[PDB]
Structure formats: C-alpha cells, structure tokens
Image: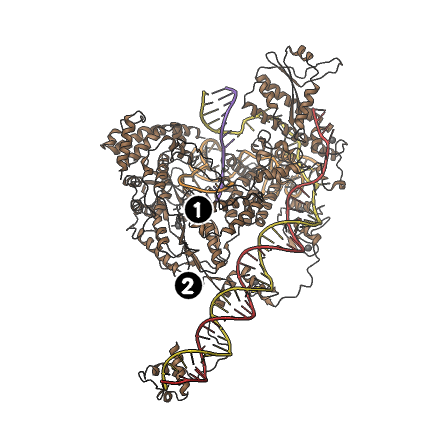
Chain colours: A brown, B red, C purple, D orange, E yellow
Amino acid sequence: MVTVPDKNPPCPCCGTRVNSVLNLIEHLKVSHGKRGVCFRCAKCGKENSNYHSVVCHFPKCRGPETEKAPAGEWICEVCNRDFTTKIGLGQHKRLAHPAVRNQERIVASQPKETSNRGAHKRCWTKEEEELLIRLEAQFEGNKNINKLIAEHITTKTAKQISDKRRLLSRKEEQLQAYYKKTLEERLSAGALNTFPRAFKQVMEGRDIKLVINQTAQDCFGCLESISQIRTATRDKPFQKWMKDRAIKKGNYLRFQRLFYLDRGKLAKIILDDIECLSCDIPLSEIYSVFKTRWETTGSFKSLGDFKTYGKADNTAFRELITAKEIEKNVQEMSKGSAPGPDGITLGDVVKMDPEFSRTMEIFNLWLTTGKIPDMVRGCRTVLIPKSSKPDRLKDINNWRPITIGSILLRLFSRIVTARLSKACPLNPRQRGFIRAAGCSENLKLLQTIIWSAKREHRPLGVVFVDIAKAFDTVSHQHIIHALQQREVDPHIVGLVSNMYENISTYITTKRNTHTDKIQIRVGVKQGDPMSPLLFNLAMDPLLCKLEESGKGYHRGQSSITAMAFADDLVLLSDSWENMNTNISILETFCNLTGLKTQGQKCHGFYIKPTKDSYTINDCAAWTINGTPLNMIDPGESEKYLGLQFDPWIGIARSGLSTKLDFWLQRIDQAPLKPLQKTDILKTYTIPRLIYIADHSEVKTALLETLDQKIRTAVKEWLHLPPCTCDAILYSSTRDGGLGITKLAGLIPSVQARRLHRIAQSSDDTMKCFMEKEKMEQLHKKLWIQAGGDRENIPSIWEAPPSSEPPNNVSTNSEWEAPTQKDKFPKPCNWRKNEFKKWTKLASQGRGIVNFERDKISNHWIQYYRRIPHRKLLTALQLRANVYPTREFLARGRQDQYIKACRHCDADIESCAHIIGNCPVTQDARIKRHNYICELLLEEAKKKDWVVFKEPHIRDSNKELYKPDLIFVKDARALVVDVTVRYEAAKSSLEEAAAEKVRKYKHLETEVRHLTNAKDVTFVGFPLGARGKWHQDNFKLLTELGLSKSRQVKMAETFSTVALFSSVDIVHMFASRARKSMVM
DNA sequence: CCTTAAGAGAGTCATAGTTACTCCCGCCGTTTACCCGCG
DNA sequence: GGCATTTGGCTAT
RNA sequence: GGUGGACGGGCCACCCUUAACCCGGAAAAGGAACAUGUGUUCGGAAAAUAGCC
DNA sequence: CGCGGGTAAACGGCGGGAGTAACTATGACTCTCTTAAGGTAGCCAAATGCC
Ligand SMILES: Cc1cn([C@H]2C[C@H](O)[C@@H](COP(=O)(O)OP(=O)(O)OP(=O)(O)O)O2)c(=O)[nH]c1=O
Ligand SMILES: [Mg+2]
Ligand SMILES: [Zn+2]
Ligand SMILES: [Zn+2]
Ligand SMILES: [Zn+2]
Ligand SMILES: [Zn+2]
C-alpha cells in the first residue's frame, strides 16, 4: 500500500527505500512477488489499483473529502444514498435497483376504492344492501309501490328509498424419367465415359443396389489405398531441484511445441483452461446411454393442421452434377476437416482426381439412382468435453456427440443440399442456417421490438422457447413427411430416406477404445451438410402456423409472431393470453411431432405499460406443458444467440472488461515468449470479443477501456515503454506493425456495416418493426466515429455496393457459379489511418514511411521463429525509436537530462548514432558491412560470376577507391558498393545509392583494365539499418541472374541481416556501457 | 564503416447533451349520493 | 531440385 | 570469500554433502503413465450449416 | 313511487411542463520515463507442389 505520490517510497515490506514508485512496484514484483499493490492518494487517501491513475489524480485532488454536503431528504431503502429530489431517488431506483423499481411500479399500478375524503355513510348496509335488491325485485308489476318498502326500511325515507332501487338498478415431368432421358442422351455421346458399363443396367434396373456398391468400392479402394501415403508422414535423482527444473522444462516443451504445431488448441488450453482430457466414463455406460437415446424411433404421429411455406421447386433437381459444381462445393467445404470412419479426407479426393471427373460420375450415378453405397452410410462419433470439472468429468452430459461422416458422403450431401435448399424456400422467419446474417437480424429485431414496446407503451410478451435435442429428436418420419408435404419430387424424397437408412456409428472415447454400432434411428445426422436444412424444413410448419394463427407483437399492419434461429425459437405477443395462444400452438406441435419442451428450460417476460413506464412480469408465469416458465425478472438476463437479454435494459452490456482482463491474465501466466503472447492475443482473444462487442452495440467508452487494457498488456509483454506509439501495435504486420486490433476503430466500423447489412436484407417483415430513423442516425454516428467521410455517408436504406460479378454471359450455371458475397462500405481503413498517424509523428516516426507496404522489409515481424526474442524486442524498439538511448530518455523532459553520447562525446545519442556514427561500434559496423558483402559475393558466385573483392583501383590523382564488390561474367563488370544506411526519410537509400554511383563513376577505363570487360555498370546497394530493403536493389539481383523467388528470399535475408546486425550493434554499445560503469 | 531535432500515451476532471424514465398538475370527462319533476 | 505459391481466426445453432 | 540452485538479476542452502523460491528479453522433460534399470505413451482427438472479421 | 333528467365531489385517463441519474461525448489538462545477459551464430519460416 504505497502513498502515491512519493519521492523515495519505502516498501510496504522489509523496508528498503526505492527511488521511484514504478521502481518500487518492480522491487515488489521481483524481490517479494506481489502483483496487487494498491496506491492511495496522499491528499484524500483515494485508493486505486492503478499507479499513474492516482498520480494524475493528485494534482487535481481537491483536498481530503471534508464536511460532506447536506444530505438530501430522500433515502434509498437498499443502499442508503441521499438525493436532492424525489425524481432523483426514483431514477436511482430505476437505474441501480431494477428489481426494486419494478415492484414499486407494480404497486403503483394497482388501483383501489379508498375514497380518502368525503365518505358519506349510507344508513343502508349489508342487511339492507341485499334486502333492497330483493324487495325491488319482489313487488314488480306494481308501479307506484314503496308503500311496503318504506315499511321495510322505515329507517330511510320515501324519495331517497326510490333513489336507492335506482342506485342499485344503475349497477409433371417425372424427374426419374428426366434423369433417365438426360443420361441416355449424354451417354449416346462420348461425354461421360468413366463408368459406361455400370450405367446401362441402371436405366432398366436389374441389380442397381450392387451397382452402387460395386462402383463405390471399385473407385474407393483407390482413394483408400492413398490414405496410407498420409499415414506414412504422420508416423511421428542427484538432487531434487533437477525434478523441478524437469517439470518446468516439460511445461515449456509442451506449450512451445503446441504453439508451432497448432497454435489453435493452445489458445484454448490457455484460455478457458479446457484440457485434453479423454472421457473416462465406462464404454458400457456411454453405449447404453447413446443406444437408448438414438436407437429409439421417434413418435411422429402426423403434422396435423400445420402446413409448409409454399410449394417445392423441382427444377433445381433436373440439371445434373457437373465437375464445376463439385469444385465449388469442395472450395466451400472446411479445409482441415477430420476424416470419417475410413480415413479419406478432402485431400485424398482432390489428389485422386484434381479435375473432378470420377467423383462427378459417381455422384451422378447415386443421384440418378436414389441410393448411396452401403460403405458410406457410416460415421464415427466422438465425445468431446464441455468443461474441465472432475465432478462433471464423471457426468454424462459434459460431452458432445460430434458425428463424423464419410467425406465423400458429406460432399454429395452438400451438393444435394444446394438443390433441396433452393427447391424448398423456408419461412422468412427462420433466420438460422439460411444465407443471411441470422444472428444479427434476430438480435436487432428483439432489441428493437423491446425498445419500441417500452417507448410506445404497448404490452409485449416474450418467451424464449427451448426445444430439447432438436436435432437428436426430430424423427426421420417427420422429415420425410415434411419433404412430401411440400410436394418435393418423390425421387429426392426417396434419396433422403435412403441417406437415412441403416446408419450406424461407434462413439470413440480414447485412442482405439471404440464402442460398437448404434443404429441411428432417430434424429438428423449431425455432421451431415443436409441436416440443418432438413431440420429447418421439419420446423417450418411451426413457424407457418405461428405466423398465420398466432397473435404476435404488432408495429403497423404486420406481426412478428415467432422469431427463429435453427432450434432456437422466441415467441412474441401483445398480451398475456395471446402469448398463451402461441404457447398452445407450440405445445400442439411438440405433442404431434415428438419434440419435447419443458417450461423449466424455457424463460420469458411480459412488459406491460403504465402511465409513466412499464412493468415486468406483473402477472402469473406462463405454463408450457404444465410446468411454469422461468420468468426473467429485472436485473436478470437470459442468453439468446450468445447475448444476455435483460428485460429491464434490453441487451445486458457486461462481461467484456472482466473477460478481457481474465484472458490477459491467463496469457501472461503461460510459458510463452513475449511475441508469442502477442500472437495468441491478437489471433485468438480479441476475435472472441468482437461478436459481443458488436451485436451488443457497445459505445466508445467500454471499447476504449478494452483497447487500453490490451495496449497495456501488450506493451508490458513486449517490454515497450508506455510512451511507445499506438501505431506499432495497431499497424498491419505488412506495414511494420504488430497487427493487434484497435477495437475503438474496428468495432464502430463493424457495427456501422452490420446496421447496413440489417437494413439491406431480404426479410420484408423484419424491415417494418425496425426504427428506420434511429438506425439511420446510429449508422451516421458510427460511420463518423469509425473515421469515415462526414459528408459521403452511404444511405443504408437505398442499396449495397459490391456487385462485381462475372456479369458477361458466364457459362457457369447457378449451381456452379461461386456464391456471391455482399461487401457493404467500410467507414475507412483504420489500419491505414493508424499508419498515417505513425508517419506524422516526428521522432518515433523517423523514416517509418519506408515500411509502408513492404513484405520483404517486414518479413521478420511475421516469421520470427529462429530469432532470440531479446533481439526481436530490440528490433521493435528500434522501429519505433523507443530504445532506451539517452536521446530517447531525454524526450520531452529535454533540458532535464543530457543527450550526449555515453561512449563518445557526440551531441545526440540517437538510435541512428549508435548504429551508424559512434566510433565505439565501428568494428561491429565493419563486420556487418563485410558480412553483407560476403552474402552478395556468395550469391553472385552461385551464378558463376567472377568477383574482385575490395579491389585496389587508382585514378590520376592516386586516389585509391575500393568498390566493395565487382561481379564479372561474360564481358560485363557490375561494380557494386554496399552501404547499410539508417533510413531517416523516404529518399534516404536512393540518396546513398546515388552517392555511391557518383563517387565511383570516375573509374571506367580503369575498371575496364582490371576486369577485362566493356560493360562497366555501377550500382549502389543501399540497405536499411532497421531492415529496409531498397526496391531498386532487385535490378542488381536481376542482373546477377537470380530467379524471382530466390530474389525475394535473398531480399528478406538481407533485410533480416541488416536489422539484426543493427540490433547487435546496439546491444554491444549498451554492454560496453554496462562493463565500463562498474569500473 | 557512417549521420546530422523533435513525445507520445495514460489517466482523471469538467461541461454539455442523451436516454429513459419520474413526478406532478390540470382538465376532462366519469362514477356516486341526493334533488327535482312526478305520473 | 530450383522455382512458385501459400499460409488464418471467432460467433450462432 | 567460493560453489550449487539449467542460464542472467535476486534470494537462498552448503562449505566437497543441496531443502525451498521470485522476476526475466532465459527456459524443447533427471516431470508423469504402460511394459524390466531401460524402450513406448503425454494426441495435431473437433463434424456440419450460415454469419462475421 | 317509479321513472327519467340534472348534480358537488373525490378520482381514473391523458396531454403537458419541468426534472434528474447514470451514461456518453468532447475538451483541457496533468502525469510517466535511468533499465539493464550475452550469445553461439548460420536465416531455417515451413509446407506443398511442379516442371
Ligand atoms: C451448439 C451446436 C448445435 N448444433 C445443432 C445440433 C444440436 O442438436 C442443436 C441444438 O441442440 P440443443 O438444443 O443445444 O440440445 P439440448 O440442449 O436440447 O440437449 P439436452 O437434452 O442436454 O438438453 O443444434 C450444431 O450443429 N453445432 C453446434 O455447435
Ligand atoms: Mg435446445
Ligand atoms: Zn522486496
Ligand atoms: Zn486525492
Ligand atoms: Zn439505492
Ligand atoms: Zn557516439
């Protein structure tokens, strides 16, 4: 507990006095091992865990908190905070105690009949309150009565009694045949030839099943025989302190081997602490569980009244599978996909047939037949954990059944998908698994609907329905019936039913510890490309009936009755009973189709308007199938599509700061090196925050806090001074930076063009519940905040740009044309803005423009494997002119300290002096220079050039010039002079080369005498002291005869050599100072 | 052999505008306990 | 066997 | 005063005998499991549909 | 005596003015820096194809 600001702060420790609070933190970290020192301001004792924060506070500290101002007369009942006015207390309760203000609103809403003032007692009472209705109904037909009533109630009078029994009175083409004709016609020609004998018995089916299997094996034992090619290359005390050193080296080994083997899964071992455990549940337990789960045919009684969205479009299936279609789908398939239960990966298929012809034949043979071979209807299931909790490592549901099918079945399934997906247009409400940003269009739709309901004072009921095991419960009969009801061609229906025939899998738990076959009789084949589409098609009836017969939230003349994303469903309503209607429809579907939903796993809420505001859950919880829902009260949240929705505030903006700090701690505690931690962060941590930080509509306050945490952590990992420019971290690795992501400049751009994407969408219903002007101005705001043109702001409600297709009559069909993506405008290139900011700095940007877009001068920043990190960090410091030279140390402080060279007596000890001018390092300089010459020498010799290393030439004035190199081959003299010059401007290396060429152009008839040649070329070979490769040097490298790949390799080698020889020069300079100070 | 000015970023603090309400007030028509005409 | 090219992440379900 | 704690800075143990540690720009197992003191293992275990950067 | 119509008198609804807590955005400031491995070297990224 330091007492910032202090001049010679004693440690809260043994007692040693350190010279600075920062040095005190260093002493605590190293000598003691405490990383949580808290700093209290000297004046007011304000405590902050961050040092300089308190340091900056101190000057503006307005003395110790004294004589607390008068306490308002409104005290909160939760935190005892005083407020000046009643409105203040109400707003505090709303903004800090939502569960309290909710109940306050509910209590205020309820009416009563108190009648506080003017309670005129009626001498009438119960005894007569009922007797008067009885007697007024007694003597009826007699008009002009009361002669008996007054006797009944003599206590009252005549006219008033008459007043009282008034008061109380007041209250087609046969796609099979089409395929046959198409084949026949194509086979009469020589177009298709691979399997001509196996196609004729298919036309008039004789042994079609065996034809499928025989063709399969006859062409698949080949691709199997080449899997072994891949398997061949994949074959790969004295003292007790030795034990601890072995453990530490083992942890190192592990992490550094994973880092270069697969940096992925190392990101996940570090972050989320999810280890490589293999499930130890007995194979009998897993066997029985998954047998009873999957080998249990569902109960799909029927689809009832539920219909589907439109009719089928069988034209998609008519035209055949062409090689370019397979190429498109293969390029659209995940590259590093694991193999099925035979080992055949995508690479096997590609190598066995680069220009897909055999596959393009077998796929057509399957499709024309409606059957698939009995060797691909198999898959290997794996149980991969969900969390590393031993008590939950002995839990069955801590594992997932990821099912891997034969890849040649996954590819055919994708090909069949494209066509089935086109032929069956899903309901526009199903935003999952469709070609669109479903998650964004659902999160925005919810957020909006809620905000608009609150603003317009309209009831809104939301239920986050939860189907249990939607993919593992949807019966195959259900899918077949759904396909039939859309009148999809019976041939494709039969093909789908056959793709769901006699499937079995084994759930491998450990290496070679497999279960045996479990016939998958229920559920969609997870891992099969068609399964998402089939699930959407079997779930469409629910959405159709909900949108046609349910009662949903209305904004105008339209009604979103049910949003959906895959199995996720959100029911909406405009009343507590309309939501009961939607829930009843959902129950009907779930009881008629076999899907199971329980209100225990479902949540919801009900926003009911009041005079001032709304109330949440001011009613009984809805019941789904009998068990009441888990109504989400204010202050609680529910995860919808990865974001926490709180009915009190819409989207719960939380977790990003805590998650980022936890991840930074996890990375810092890893046995990784300074530039490996930066890679793990910029490639596997910041991306994880994008989704939440984008779809949650985070502002530039949290974005700046997160970016500040990232910057501090990175600059501490890399041992860069805090004053180092942001550009080096945020500039692209192609421009000399580290490539770290600037969230404050990225997330606004992502949000702006996400809003653009939502506005420019196909969901017509979705773009009616959307607040047009609010998102228009929000898009303008984010565009300006992202650094865009404040005048040329695109109109999100007009059209996108992109386009740029193969517009001119492309022979590619619609199934072969590569899928076109949409490219909405970006506000700006924030990375280029960061680099421009770098270039504008005058001291840390010295000559940085030479690294504008150079991949051969920044090759080391990306590929730094075999370089001591102590060298890499110094290279980074040199590139930003933040190396602790006395010139840099006396920055801003200026006169405060001396900038003179510590070794020589030069005016400024700039980073350029140490590398280029100081006599002390002259030896090293010479070595480096000669070394570079030698490299060039060797390169020239590899092309059989004669070399005159440092020749002794003399002119008339006896002025001996010594051109570093002279290459000669076939009557030519390439005089070359190497020079490693610090780059302090865009035209620095050019100037050096010009100087060399001008100072050696005197010797023409002298070089002719020495070299025995007539073509006396003169070239300067400038190199950057910080690793800048002059582009014109390629000319020389071309004259030597180097290839265009060895040219780039040698350019990278030269840049690396120059940079890391300058680093060594700087290190020698500092080490000489170190070795001389002790004297 | 070579070069030859530089602060930059991190952090509070103050001021002004926004969002999502809070609060009350007046009016405005509406219920409720006798009044009047009353056949 | 020199040359030419290429080379990732995250989110929802 | 010197050695050892892989290496540097500490800080410890011993006086050739080594128990415990901290930080690092250093750290590729004298660590665990299966077989008889020696070899093997420590998995690159991860699918699909869309989206995003 | 019943039946119509009027009725102050608190009070349910709805516009309207004023009002504030907690953010959200912009700007003006003010604060920090002195530490501390040397090193064989041998540029290999590293993989994959291709001709
Ligand atoms: C998360 C996830 C889901 N899906 C699909 C398959 C899943 O069956 C479906 C969602 O299933 P869930 O609804 O998450 O399964 P469940 O929670 O109902 O199971 P439980 O009985 O334990 O309650 O979405 C994927 O294809 N990939 C994924 O990564
Ligand atoms: Mg579910
Ligand atoms: Zn200490
Ligand atoms: Zn203070
Ligand atoms: Zn409070
Ligand atoms: Zn000098």
A169 to A689, vertically: above or below? below
| Front residue of A928 and A530 | A530
Which element type, helix, strand or loop, lies under badge 2? loop
Q: Mark 2 or mark 1: which is in front?
A: 1
Quarter residue A319 falls in:
top left
Give the chain letter at badge 1. A
Whole-percent x and y of residue A535? 36, 46
A617 to A52, vertically: above or below? below
| Front residue of A764 and A244 | A764
Which element type, helix, strand or loop, lies under badge 1? helix
Label drawn at residue A620: 2
Residue drawn at x 61%, y 44% as measured from the top left = A712
* Quarter of the render that holds ligand 5: bottom right
Looking at the rendered structure, the kind of residue marked 1 is Gly
Looking at the rendered structure, the kind of residue marked 2 is Ala
Few, some or many residues within 10 Å of mark 2 (<14, 14–19, 20+):
few
Label drawn at residue A438: 1
| Front residue of A273 and A1002 | A1002
A1011 to A494, vertically: above or below? above
Horizontal side, residue A749 vs residue A38: left or right:
left
